[PDB]
Image: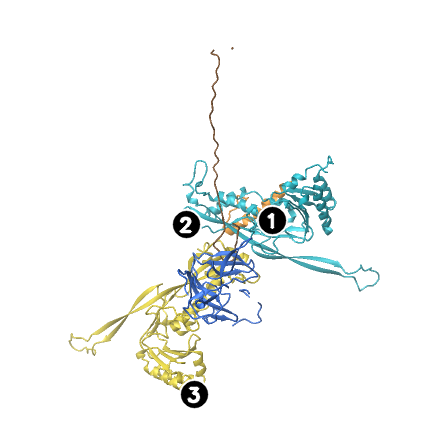
Chain colours: A yellow, B brown, C cyan, D orange, E blue
Amino acid sequence: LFDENYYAKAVANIIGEVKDPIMYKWFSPDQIEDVDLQMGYQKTVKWDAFLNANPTTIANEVNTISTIGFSSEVVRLNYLKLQYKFRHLKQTSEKFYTSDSYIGDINNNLLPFAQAYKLASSEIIKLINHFVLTGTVSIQKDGKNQKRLLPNMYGLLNMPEQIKEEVASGDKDKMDKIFEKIEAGLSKLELGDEFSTPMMVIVDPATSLKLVKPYACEKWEDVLIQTIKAINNREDVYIETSNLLKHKILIYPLNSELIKFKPSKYMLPTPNEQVDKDSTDVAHSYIDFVLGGLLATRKTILQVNIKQS
Amino acid sequence: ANPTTIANEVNTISTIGFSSEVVRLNYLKLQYKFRHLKQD
Amino acid sequence: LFDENYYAKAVANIIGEVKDPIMYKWFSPDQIEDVDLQMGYQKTVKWDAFLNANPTTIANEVNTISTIGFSSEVVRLNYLKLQYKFRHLKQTSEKFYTSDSYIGDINNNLLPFAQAYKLASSEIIKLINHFVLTGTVSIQKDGKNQKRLLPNMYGLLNMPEQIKEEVASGDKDKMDKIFEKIEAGLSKLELGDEFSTPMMVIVDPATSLKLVKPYAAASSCEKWEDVLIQTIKAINNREDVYIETSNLLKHKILIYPLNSELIKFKPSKYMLPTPNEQVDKDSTDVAHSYIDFVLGGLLATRKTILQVNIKQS
Amino acid sequence: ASLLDSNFVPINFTEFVQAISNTYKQRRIQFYENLKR
Amino acid sequence: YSKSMIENKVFSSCFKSKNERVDAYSFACSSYTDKIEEYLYDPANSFPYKRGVKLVPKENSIYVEVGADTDMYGICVDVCEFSCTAYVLPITNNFEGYLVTRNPSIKIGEILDINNNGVIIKAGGGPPTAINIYALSDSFTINSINLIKVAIFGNRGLEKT
């Protein structure tokens, strides 16, 4: 194949220079499990067992024994396939654009295929990270002109049937009010017998700036970490800052029994076999990726939104 | 038409046409009759 | 590659049947040097030296010696890539259009790829020769609707800063007046220190026909051509003079030396027609192919080309 | 690396183009060798 | 002016809103089977980049010059300044991309018209529009030139007001 497909050879040789997605920091190693599906839906069945009565004491002769029942639940997850197109120079034409210490037309903004693919993959990975964190797809800073997505395609911030807290616009600068809302949400959190697990908190830069203020020689961050340790059996509590969030606070456990990410094994950018060619030196290539696959149990994510208006 | 300058992207390009001419040569038969003495 | 690309195989098999360009006769072998470029510009630097003072006599002990300076000039040349397209028959479809005497569709003007490529290459070579000689690209006999070219892209006929002479309309048949103008131009020629070199003259067919008349009362044993050759030898240090006839010229006489130090041709190594890899295909029997060629690369020193134009109107 | 040598076998289109250019150069050189003004 | 426009002492400083560049790729959504043509343009009269152009057959070649919607041949999507060559998408083809406008305050969904300078303006100026142009985004200023995302699909049957 590499004897015939120069583009495949270049992708193989430069695939290692693409940095790892930052979304890996928001999940434990066990929480992520790949699936084999490009586009469509997949039904996951979860089995459980329960006790019908008290156990039976084995003494002398007896035939009537207590029973153990079973139950099942079916969850459907939707996966979507998306594509991008980019222009690049042609392999037989790169020799006429190999300048000193660089290749490509500065005037025409044309690059060799390897560099073009690397940059496009980086941008697509950024988009995928934004979707996983927020659940929306947009390319504007205002978050408008969103691409409409299918049902059963949720992110951490917009997952339904979770704890949602709202801080009024009049209390947007009152860390005491924000922490009161956080405590109420933590009280409403329901982890059951899986409480002994590390917890993850994601905050916006403004909330990060507010957290390091003195508590009203203790910090709001320290108080929050202690409060979360009170509920998670004093496991680890990780704090992360993301520029993809705005006046939002996300708190959720890192337990694979409560929240699981089942992405398609084609989620990350992959080249397409089709390459547009003509008589000129410019060619076009396509990159494919897949979105969807976040599954969570009910009332295990706390989402605090601080209204600005 | 004039040739096309290949810079950046373009798919509309001047063409070169061809033609076929058929040359035909005609050959015609003609005859004369003359009188003579049998074997003045 | 030949086991996969029939078009490439056929081009390789039939490339030898395209005749050499006629522009090769207008230059000496040393005057032509290929360059590796398709589109863009290329710079050439020429270095010169000069003496600052009289030489120093070396006697006894001397520390101060006369110096020799240096200077440079930079010349920029432009190259342009051009392409043509042509339709032909698909390789697998030739058997259904084969005939007892030929191959192809006469009623629809469809040829096999090899013949179509040969004809297109011949036409493009004619166009390239015309551009090299005249400095302009056009497909009309009137010479209008010219393709706009880049700066620093000239031919032998439109190179700036040369000697230009114009024979008036009323003297369009007076060979004596034509020679008067030619002598004035040859006097105005400035070859510097490279004057001892062969010269080349290119004339239109009408001027060539006028040049074989007896010299003018008419004289015997001497022609106007001989008189012109002697006049040119008066300035080229009695070196060789070559005369050529080209139908591309019209009422023009072009005189220039065949010395690489004065006039040089640095064409792109892809100047002559080259097939393109892309071949348009569909469900029918008709396919399309593309031919590329590069123009540009004539460099000449100033005031070394004489251009005499005989006016008709 | 020229089309004149029948032993030459191109591997790809770039080699084919280089062979075409070399063939053109060789033909020009041969023309100048055989030219007699 | 030009598209590329220069040595810098320092480099210029998320993925969102990085397409707001004068030399950005004109087609927001491209497609094979889009016809692109090459023409010459006047190098001293008007710079046709990202403007509606018209065919002017001159005595030496066919040029493209900035023109109005009434006599528009297409949209100039790219220019090669080295050869002074303009690349044109004919009006018979659809377009969805960024074009030059003169009004810094245009909202989304508004009807638009191309003026004599090949510039997007509001269709309420009074001239009867003959092309279907709609604003897909608010106009943004690059500091100064105003650009806007538009969708152009063919001619309009009856000229509007």
Mark nearest the camera among 2 and 3 is 2
Crowding at dot 1, Cα within 10 Å, few <14 / some 14-19 / many 20+, comes out as many
Quarter of the rendering containing residue C89: top left
> Hey, what amino acid is under mark 1?
Val
Whole-percent x, y for residue A10 in the image: 47, 60
Rounded to the nearest whole Å, what is the CA distance between mark 1 and mark 3? 85 Å
Secondary structure under badge 1?
Answer: helix
Tag 2 near tag 1, CB within 8 Å: no
Residue positioned most to the top: B40
Is residue C277 in sight in this rendering? Answer: yes
**Outermost residue toward the bottom?**
A216
> Which chain is home to disc 1?
C
The kind of residue tagged 2 is Asp
Q: Name the residue under label 2.
A: C282
Label 1 with label 3: CB-CB less than 8 Å: no
Q: Position of residue E60 (x, y in %)?
A: 56, 53
Q: A226 or A131: which is nearer to us?
A: A131
- Residue A215: which disc? 3
Mark positioned earlier in the residue sequence (2 or 1): 1
Q: Which of marks 1 and 3 is in front?
A: 1
What chain letter is assigned to the residue under label 2? C
Q: Do labels 2 and 1 share a chain?
A: yes
Residue closest to the eye, C164 or C196: C164
Q: Name the residue under label 1.
A: C132
For disc 2, the neighbor class at 10 Å (few under 14, some 14 to 19, many from 20) is: few
Estimate the spatial distance between the alpha carbons at disc 2 and disc 3, rounded to whole Å: 75 Å
Secondary structure, mark 3, is: loop
